[PDB]
Amino acid sequence: GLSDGEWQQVLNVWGKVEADIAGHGQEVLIRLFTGHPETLEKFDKFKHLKTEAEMKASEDLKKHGTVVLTALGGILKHKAHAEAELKPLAQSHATKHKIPIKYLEFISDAIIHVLHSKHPGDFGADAQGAMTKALELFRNDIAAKYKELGFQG
Amino acid sequence: GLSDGEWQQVLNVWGKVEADIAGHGQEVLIRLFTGHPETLEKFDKFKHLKTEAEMKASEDLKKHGTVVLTALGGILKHKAHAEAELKPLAQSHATKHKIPIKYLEFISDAIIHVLHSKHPGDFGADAQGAMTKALELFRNDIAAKYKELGFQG
Ligand code: HEM
Ligand code: HEM
Ligand code: NI
Ligand code: NI
Ligand SMILES: [O]
Ligand SMILES: [O]
């Protein structure tokens, strides 16, 4: 994964992109299409463009550039925030508390038991299946950080 | 992973949890401790507590239950939001646009060059090292979604 400061580096340069997301988007796609022409053939609405000049002139190529960098920006900002929130918890449970993944499984089953007992109206079979998958994904994230830190959990 | 409706089911039952986080946190730790006595040994503050009635009387156990469900809740809500943002992107690039992972490596290459070219003051060796790793994490997330969908590309 990235460190705390590694994400801050990423978000700082991303702010600069957002000051002219249109121009950045355009240049990224044109650099892609010139360096790797086979990428242009995946785009039914752009593959007619032959020259740099035609590409720079395309209103919709510039609009698509914005759509791509906006979506990627949103994803990176969520990853940064999510990592900063998870890594402290993973570190303390790995190093200080030394909690095996097995014990995270037990507390996952305890949550599902309590939600079945107290909220069956918003916890039918489907919603229970959903929570079981959700808590497994959470354990998997922790297990991934445990490995990064070389704690056998 | 979870479908759109499954994440909504998770968020919907979590809303009920957060409405009585005190009581739910207590019931989760009592269920864990009574089902798996070994887990009580990890808790210096609680390991003397011998019965549900003792555990229910512990103000410390209640406060810890709140800290646990508060931390978990934040992680689940972020995961639901990020997945609902990522899953459609991966779905469309796999099944509609048919974009191999190697082409996301190409566009990552172009994003690095455009950032180095236009914002070098904000894009030194470390900043560029950070962005390179961050774009890898993005491609790995799409790659993990493609594998789920049995798209090789
Ligand atoms: C950082 C990488 C990428 C991001 C964030 C991104 C994002 C997007 C978004 C948000 C859309 C519109 C919604 C959708 O159809 O899912 C889209 C459409 C599309 N993307 Fe991507 N994309 C990326 C990489 C690529 C690459 C490398 C290719 C092809 C070589 C590609 C080909 C397409 C195509 C063909 C469309 C459909 C465009 C249309 O509506 O005519 N994408 N992309
Ligand atoms: C959903 C699972 C879990 C969550 C979200 C969680 C969260 C937390 C948080 C936020 C803290 C306080 C800050 C910290 O030290 O990181 C904490 C402390 C702790 N956790 Fe966990 N925890 C989980 C599972 C477990 C399990 C299963 C055990 C043991 C079986 C455990 C043992 C501890 C201990 C011993 C502490 C320190 C308690 C204290 O000194 O007051 N945790 N946990
Ligand atoms: Ni978002
Ligand atoms: Ni948060
Ligand atoms: O794209
Ligand atoms: O915990």
Image (cartoon, coloured by chain):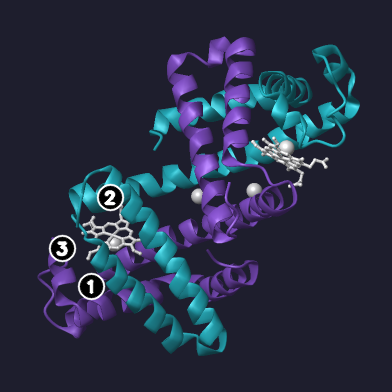
Chain colours: A purple, B cyan
Residue, x 72% and y 18% (percent of image)? B34
Residue hosting label 3: A42
Determine if the C-beta at disc 3 is less than 8 A from ligand 1. yes
| Res. B123 in view | no
The answer as to whether the residues below labels 2 and 1 share one chain is no
**Separation of residues labelled 2 and 1 (CA atoms):** 31 Å
Is A130 placed left or right of B95 in the picture?
right
Label 2: which secondary element:
helix
Question: B31 or A25: nearer the eye?
Answer: B31
Of residues A44 and A36, the one nearer the viewer is: A36
* Left/right of residue B109 with respect to residue B115 in the rendered view: left
Query: Looking at the image, can residue A40 be seen?
Result: yes
**Residue B31, placed above or below residue B106:** above
Which residue was labeled with disc 1? Answer: A58
**Residue neighbourhood size for the residue with mark 3, other residues' Cα within 10 Å, grouped as few (<14), some (14–19), many (≥20):** few
User: Does residue B142 lie above or below B47 as drawn?
Assistant: below
Q: Amino acid at mark 1?
A: Ser
